[PDB]
Amino acid sequence: MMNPINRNPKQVPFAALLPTLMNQLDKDRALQLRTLYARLKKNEIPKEGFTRHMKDIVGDQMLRMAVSKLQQVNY
Image 1 (cartoon, rainbow, N blue to C red):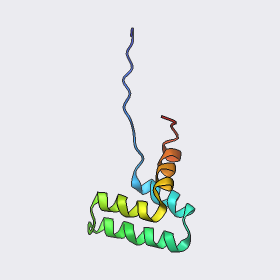
Image 2: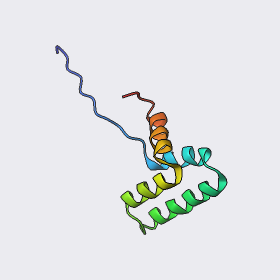
Image 3: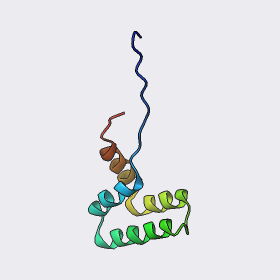
């Protein structure tokens, strides 16, 4: 407590999630993700929509694993 250290959580961007996921996805799935991102860029779908849709493509398990590896932090 002599020298308190403040730490804050950090999250990786979706931009870095695409290539990681695309590498773990088949070309057909990767193409779906690619066009899905385009929808996000065009703002035709909400961020929640993007996340939800992404989960439907890679899966919740892959989604949490992808960010876990990118974060590379157990906690």
